[PDB]
Image: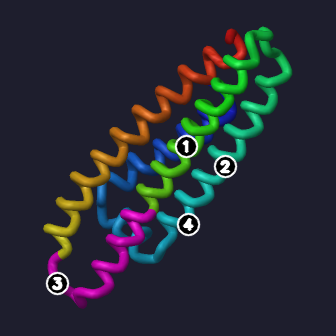
């Protein structure tokens, strides 16, 4: 697929691993390497998405401009939604790190169950927003 889709796919791969919540995952969550890596992948995805929209604007089927400006507005909204979803994933993981650090050496198991359920819901949101964004891009130049 497109460059931004490949960047998002790297985000997906890393997040799927994180969602296993293994001991390797826990190590990288508590050191903040997970959230730094997710930051980098998210920024790359958004950068490539902006560049891709800009290149799509070079091959537009001219429509009522009415329609073109409205569709550009909607596409920017979808982009912002994707960025915010990825930031919500990262922030939930930051929260988990802070909670684990606050409880000395006690069991994190209940924290991990709650985190896993919340991450499944955050992934569902990010995925439906990504699919919406792909469809808006696909129809963008077609008008």
Residue plotted at (65% across, 25% down): 70
Choose the circle earlier in sequence order: 1 or 2: 1
- Which residue carries the number 2 mark? 44
- Which residue carries the number 3 mark? 106
Find residue 65 and report its image quarter: top right
Say if mark 3 contacts mark 1, CB within 8 Å: no
Find residue 73 and report its image quarter: top right
Decide whether residue 102 is among the magenta residues: yes
Question: Between 14 and 117, which is closer to the camera in this rendering?
Answer: 117
Judge the density around disc 4: few (<14), some (14-19), many (≥20) Cα neighbours within 10 Å.
some
Provide the major secondary structure of the magenta segment: helix
Residue 88: percent from left, percent from top: 43, 57
From which residue to which does the magenta span run? 91-107
Say if mark 3 contacts mark 2, CB within 8 Å: no
Question: Can you say which quadrant of the picture contains the C terminus?
Answer: top right
Say if mark 1 contacts mark 2, CB within 8 Å: yes
- Which residue carries the number 1 mark? 10
Choose the circle earlier in sequence order: 3 or 1: 1
Find residue 25 and report its image quarter: bottom left
Distance between mark 1 and mark 2 Cα atoms:
10 Å
Question: Which label sits in the foreground, 3 or 2?
Answer: 2
Kindly identify which numbered label has been placed on residue 36. 4
120 sits left or right of 61 in the view: left
Look at the numbered disc 2 and give the secondary structure of its residue.
Answer: helix
Image height check: is 72 above or below 138?
below
Residue plotted at (23% across, 86% down): 103
């Amino acid at each position: 697929g497109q460059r931004w889709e490949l960047a998002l796919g790297r985000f997906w791969d890393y997040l799927r691993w994180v969602q296993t919540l293994s001991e390797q995952v826990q190590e990288e969550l508590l050191s903040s390497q997970v959230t730094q890596e997710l930051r980098a992948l998210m920024d790359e995805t958004m950068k490539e998405l902006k560049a891709y929209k800009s290149e799509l604007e070079e091959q537009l089927t001219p429509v009522a401009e009415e329609t073109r400006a409205r569709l550009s507005k909607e596409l920017q909204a979808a982009q912002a939604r994707l960025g915010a979803d990825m930031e919500d994933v990262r922030g939930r993981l930051v929260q988990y790190r802070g909670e684990v650090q606050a409880m000395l050496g006690q069991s994190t198991e209940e924290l991990r169950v709650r985190l896993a359920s919340h991450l499944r819901k955050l992934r569902k949101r990010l995925l439906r927003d990504a699919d919406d964004l792909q469809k808006r891009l696909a129809v963008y130049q077609a008008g």
